[PDB]
Each structure stands twice: as structure tokens, then as C-alpha cells.
Amino acid sequence: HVLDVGFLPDMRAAASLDTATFSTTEMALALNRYLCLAVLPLITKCAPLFAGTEHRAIMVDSMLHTVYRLSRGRSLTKAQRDVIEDCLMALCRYIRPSMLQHLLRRLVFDVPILNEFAKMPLKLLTNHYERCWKYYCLPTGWANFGVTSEEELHLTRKLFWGIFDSLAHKK
Amino acid sequence: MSFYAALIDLLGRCAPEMHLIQAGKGEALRIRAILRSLVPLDDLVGIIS
Amino acid sequence: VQFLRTDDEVVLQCSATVLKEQLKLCLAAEGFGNRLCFLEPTSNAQNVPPDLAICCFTLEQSLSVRALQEMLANTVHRTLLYGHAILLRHAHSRMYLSCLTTSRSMTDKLAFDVGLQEDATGEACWWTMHPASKQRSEGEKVRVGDDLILVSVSSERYLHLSTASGELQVDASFMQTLWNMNPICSCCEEGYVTGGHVLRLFHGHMDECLTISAADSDDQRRLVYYEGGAVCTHARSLWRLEPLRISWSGSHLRWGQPLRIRHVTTGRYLALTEDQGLVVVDACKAHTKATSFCFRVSKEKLDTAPKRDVEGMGPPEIKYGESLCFVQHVASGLWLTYAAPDPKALRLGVLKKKAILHQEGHMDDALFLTRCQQEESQAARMIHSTAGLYNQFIKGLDSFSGKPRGSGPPAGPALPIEAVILSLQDLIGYFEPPSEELQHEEKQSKLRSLRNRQSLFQEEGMLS
Amino acid sequence: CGGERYLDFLRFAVFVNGESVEENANVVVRLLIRKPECFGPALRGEGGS
Amino acid sequence: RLQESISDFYWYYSGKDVIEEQGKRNFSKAMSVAKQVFNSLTEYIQGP
């Protein structure tokens, strides 16, 4: 079922401004993502739907076509539950969505990315997990994210309070 | 397609609640079995596909 | 009477329009070996009599819906009323009619199978009656010979007679079908002979009975003898009486009433073929002009024409024990007696008295009737069914036993693999020894019953 | 079209405030199953596509 | 008909140990009508 529903959104259902006439897919998103959240069976192994997770991340991150904050919240919760349910199965499936956050750390839509990349280490803490080249880029990502905080556009208290990353797992 | 979609939506909305199933209520499982035999799972899986 | 009280014997009859004129069929089930139910035709009883042994059903309870629900929630002669839930118990096997959670029809139609259950526990063994066309009302009392519809409780489906690609099968679907419960019998008087009872026909003293030839005989077990001695305990001397009437075929026997005598072990009917004498014949060649017999005291009596058919239980006159009567044919009108053609020194038989039909018989041929136990009759019926099934299996095995398969695995009819497996399991459970934790007296009684059942099964074969 | 219009009304008598009423859903299910023609020419029975 | 209804009510309330207030109210309001019907039936016979 997840394999079949994975390929319905083609590049976030063509999030680029092309037609803006068929938004019923976004409507059915709020109906099927709830069922997807109702279960957490994709935990053990045999998970080649990393492209599906990337598609979901690009769908929540790109809301150019018929933006709706109400359904954006449902997609936000879907992504949060998906990340909090399973992890440490690969390395690219997390850094690639977080590449935008590492580069564009001042984006207003990066709060999902920061929240997920923060919730993952307290939930894991390297226990039953092996570091790799992905773990080697965490210092650079943390450094640039911190540098963007105080250099330009001094962040307000609301976002600065939520931008307190753990920055754990040193060496 | 609209008529079948509406009929399936009505049949799903008439399904017994989960706590009714988990707390006995043999009539609830009787209705659930009737709905189960009405339409198989493969039909739904193909419909979504 | 004629009110369908509790604890009477009934048969579920239905009408089918598949045939050009009409068809009457009665619901039936084998019991052991096959849990499913099937319809048995009855309108064609002029030449082929029906098997009424496995057709009778007994009404156990007739509680209301609320009382039934309370009883089910609390697990561990009331007049029948419309809207009540009833429990039906099979007469032959101590099994309860129920709607099984299975289906094989190639068309779902929300239809299940109608079968039998070993125990009354559960919800699928109860059927709620509903009125027919609006000549009655909910809560009104139910009369015999009145059409009605039966609704299952667990499946909420009618007892429907399907007209699918099959040939007149019975299932539990949402299509409406009308059934009526013809009352076979009712409250019967103690020690009186009624139609349908399996019994032994004793002659003269208590050491002679009307039996049939034993197994492994020179003939095809179609010669009627007058053997005595240890044969009185075996199942050979077990005969049953089938009145030509179909609705009230459980009433007290009447003098001169036409009846058919059937051997339960073999399934053959006593008849006169005018070719070999008084012999038992197959059910197909069992026309009423050759199979109908009767009992009457006062042998000659200047017999008159029988009349005055009774549409009820009737008065009881033929009493068990003291029933010294004479058997004669109705269509022809000749009596029967012991032949004894010659007292040969080397006859190699204790009596070996063949049964023959004569216009005027000898003296001392009056037969008095004694009934057999329920266990003996049930064992005889199981012996008959099991022997038939195993003979069919052996014939199916031997049809293909010669030519290798190569291609086209079905050479002929398919072997009843599932039926024979179920029959074997049922027989294994049947002969289970009693547990060792029972009390001494009851354990000894159960051991005696098991030994008697084993001896009865072995006498009619079932080992060869 | 008439089937869809009639099924629209029944969706409000069995599903209220996200929950489901047991009695109305049960009686609707029994009435629907007792008349198989309401399910359309596909979910009727023998010969159904 | 009223007797059948009362029997059904008793069958429904058999499982519970103590009948609540609402069941007792309906039982009383049915028994009052039963008493009235019984009185009407008696008046048909008295005065032989």
C-alpha cells in the first residue's frame, strides 16, 4: 500500500507553478496521511521508500501550489511522526533533506528540518547506531547554522527559543 | 464511479467503533463480518491502486 | 393437536418450481461423515421411497429473542409462537442444525452454508421463525401445515433453496424461501408401535426372529431367512417401518395399514418380485405394488376394504410385546410363513428356514414385535452409511488401479477424500475408550456399551 | 445519479460529530443487505463484474 | 400484548441485580395500565 501511494506525488505533485487546477491531491493528502500516521510498521528493515520520505519532505517544504496552513500542519505532523518512528537505516535520506537547512539556515520553512534534526539525536544518542561521513558533516552544519544566527538578521526570541539544538555526540 | 464511492463511504461510516469491538458486543462483530463479506480487501487495494 | 408444540418430530419441506409441474423436497443431513445438508425429493415416492431416517428433526427449545440472549450471555412443551427462536436437533445423530461459517458456490451473494454442529453451545444453532404472507401476525401461535420463513441468528440470513448452476442445493442467503414443518410425530403412548421405529420381528417364542442372511454369503444378501439364536443381538434383525403417508408418518400403527419394511443395515426394502419370491430389493425398484405390507390379527376374518385415514396421532392399538399379528401383501394378498422345504441331515444350518409368500400359510407364523434401543439403531445406521462410503471408495480406487495415469489424472469419479477422512475421524472419536478417572460403576457401564458397539460393528463387517 | 443523491442523505443519519450511532447504523445495514439491488449492478450477486 | 411486553422487559432486566430508577418508572407505568385492563375485564364478568 505504501509502495502504491508513494508515487502519486510526482515532485511534490509538480509543486512548480504549472497548472494550479488539480489540487484535489492535496485534499486527499489530509485523508491518507492520517491513516499513514495511525500505524508505525516501517521500523525493522527492507525500506527502499527513502525516495518517498524525500518526496514527503519536499511536499511539506514546497507549498507553492494552493498553499494551506491547515493541511500544512497535518503534513508537518506526518513528517514528525515518520522521523520519530524510525531512523538509523541509512545516511543520505536525512542529510539530503537537511542540505537545504545546512545551506539556507535562515529559511522560515526550515523549522520542520531543525525540529527533526534535533529530535533525532536525543532519541538515538548514537546508541545502536554507527557514525559515518554523514556524522562528519554535523560539525559543519552546526557551525554554519550557529553563524547564521547572530551575524545577520538577529533572530527574535520566539524562533531563537526553538532554535536551541542539542549539538551533542562530540569526539 | 460516484455512486459506488458514496455507497462505500456510507458502508464504512456504518462500521462499529473500535472500542465496541474490543469490549464484546457480538452484534458489532456480526455487522463487521457482514461488511467484510460484502466486499473483499483486494477490491479496495486495487481501487486505491 | 395440529399445533406444533415443543418436543415433536418435524421435517422441513420446501417447494421447487425447477421441474415443469412442481417438486417437493425435505431438508436432510447424513450426520457423521458429512456435516453439510441437502434436499431429498419426496413427490416421486410412487416407485422410489425417500430416506426418512435422516430427515426427522426434533424441536428442543422455543425461547423468545430476549430469553435467548440472556441464556447465551449467562452460559457457564411450550407452544410454538411466531417471532421465537428455535433449536433443532437431528433425529439420527445427536447434532444440532446450524449455519456454518463456510461457503462454496462460486457466487458470494452473502451466502453461507447450512450444516450440523456437535453441540448446542453457540449462537449459530438457533433459528427465529417469521410469519408468511399477512394471514398471521407477530406473536401469534403457529399451526401445522402453515408456511413460514426461518431466519438465522448468527448469520441473519434465510434458509434458502438455491437455483444456481448446481442441482437444488440449500444454503443461508438473503433470498426469501418458504418452508413448512410437517409434524412427523407427537407425544406417543408408552409401549406402542409407531411408524419409523427400528425393531425386531420375533416369531412364536422369544428365541426366533425374522432376520436376513449374514455377510460373506453366497448370494448378494437378498435372501430372507428365519435364523434364531445369537442373531437376535446383532444388527441383522433390525427392521424399520415406513408408512406410505409422508406428513404424519409417526402415528400409532393401525391394523391393515400399508407399510414398507426396510433393512437398516443394507438399505433394501422387503418385496415380492414374482421372479424369486419374498426377497429384499433396491430402493429404485421399490414400487408400492410390490413393497407394501401390513399387520393384522385374525388371519382370515373375512377381511374388508381399509378406509378412514387418520390426520393425527390416532388411537394406539398395536402394543409392543403382545402384538401377535400376521403380515400380508396388499396389492396381491398372500401371506408369509416358514418354508422348510426339507429337513436335510446335512443342511449345515441351525434353522435355515427361507421366507416365502403363500396364498394360505401354515400355522404358528404370527409375529410379535419388540423394539430396539436407540444406540443399536444409531449404530446400524452408521454401519450402513460407513459401509456404503467405504465400498464407493474401494470401487473408485479399483477403477484406476489398473492403468497408470500418464495424463488426465481423473479416470472417473473423484475419490471422496475429505468425506472418508471425516468419517475416519468420527469413527475414531466414536470408539474412544472411557477415561480412567470415572467412577467404577459408570466406567464399567461405558465399557460394556463400547464392547457392544464394537461387536455390532464387527458383526456386519467393518473389519474386512 | 439518484442512487448517489439518496445515499447522500443516509450518510448524515449514521455519522454525527465523527462518531457513529449504533442503532441507526445497524438498521440501515440490515435494510441495505436485505435488498441487494441497492448496491448497484456490480455488487448484486451472480454475474456481477 | 401488554403481558408479552412486560415479560420482555423482565427478560431484559434479569441480568442486572438492581433495577435503576428509569426502569422502575416504566414498570410502574405499565403495571398501572395492566391493573386498569384487569379491572375492565373483571367488570365484564361480575354480575354473572
Image: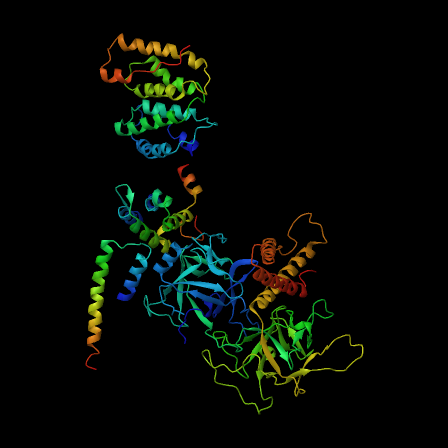
Where does residue C59 sit, x and y in percent of width and height? Answer: 44, 66
Q: Report whether A99 appears left or right of C290.
A: left
Q: How many marks?
A: 0
Which of A114/A120 is in front? A120
Left or right: where C367 falls relative to D41: right
Give the left or right position of residue C271, taking residue A90 as reference. right
Q: Is residue C387 above or below residue C280?
A: above
- Tell which residue pokes out farthest to the front in this image: C440
Tell me the quadrant of the picture where the C terminus of chain C can be found: bottom right
- Who is closer to the viewer here, C181 or B21? B21
Task: Judge whether residue C19 can be spotted in this image.
Answer: no
Q: Quadrant of the N terminus of chain C?
A: bottom left
Q: Spot the residue most to the right.
A: C346
How are the colours assigned in the image? Answer: rainbow
Residue C253 placed where, x, y %? 52, 80
Where in the figure is residue C132, as x and y percent of width and height? Answer: 36, 67
Q: Residue furthest bottom?
A: C302
| Residue D25, placed above or below residue C329 | above
Classify residue C205 as left or right of residue C254.
right
Query: Residue E46: which quarter of the image?
Result: bottom left
- Residue C447 in the image: state x and y as whole percent: 61, 61
Q: Which is nearer the eye, A63 or E41?
A: E41
Q: Is residue E44 visible?
A: yes
C232, above or below C89, in the image: below
Residue at 35% x, 21% y: name it.
A119
State the residue at coordinates (43%, 14%): A134
